[PDB]
Image (spheres, rainbow, N blue to C red):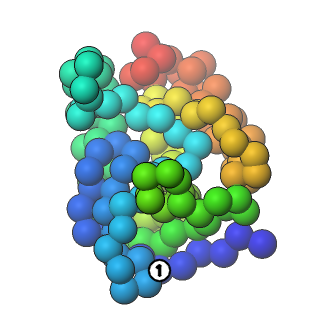
Amino acid sequence: KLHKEPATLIKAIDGDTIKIMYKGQPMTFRLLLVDTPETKHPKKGVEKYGPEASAFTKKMLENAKKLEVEFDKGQRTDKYGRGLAYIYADGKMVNEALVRQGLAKVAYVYKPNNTHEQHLRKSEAQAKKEKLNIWS
């Protein structure tokens, strides 16, 4: 069953990509199942809510007493060598918080990495009904 492990923030890069110290090593992590608008983009530039999703993630992680990472049951790294996980700040999942606030859409899902898909989908529909940010 999925279990949490300790990690240490190094640097938030943007809304859904962060650098953390994981088991002694610095790595880049990508937040599972969510897409935040982009600040660092090749073609297009800062997308709308990009700067916002990324301040959110930054504040949430920097203010936490405790950071934990939760791997899903599939591949734990993507083709760019980024960890793939659910991230928790004092017990609150960053991935769901982003979605609940209308600052992320639920991503395209790849089984078997999809254990919190329903919950997340729950929160996105609520942010939709409340027409928050993305959904305004």
Above or below for 60 versus 55: below
The residue at which mark 1 appears reads as 6
Mark 1, secondary structure of its residue: strand
Of all residues, the one furthest to the bottom in this rendering is: 24
Closer to the camera, 23 or 4?
Answer: 23
Residue drawn where x is 27% and y is 55% of the image = 12
Residue 23 in percent (x, y) is at: 43, 84
**Looking at numbered disc 1 in the image, what kind of residue is underneath it?**
Pro
**Does any portion of residue 93 appear in the rendered image?**
no
Residue drawn where x is 23% and y is 34% of the image = 40
**Does any portion of residue 80 appear in the rendered image?**
yes
Above or below for 56 versus 83: above
Residue drawn where x is 26% and y is 51% of the image = 13
The image quadrant of residue 4 is bottom right
**Label 1 Cα crowd, 10 Å radius (few <14 / some 14-19 / many 20+):** few
Closer to the camera, 11 or 131?
Answer: 11
Q: Quadrant of the C terminus?
A: top left
Q: Quadrant of the N terminus?
A: bottom right
Left or right, 8 with respect to 131, comes to left
Closer to the camera, 34 or 43?
Answer: 43
Residue 41 in percent (x, y) is at: 26, 28
Of all residues, the one furthest to the top in this rendering is: 136
Closer to the camera, 119 or 74?
Answer: 74
Left or right, 118 with respect to 105, comes to right
Residue 71 in percent (x, y) is at: 61, 65
The image quadrant of residue 29 is bottom left
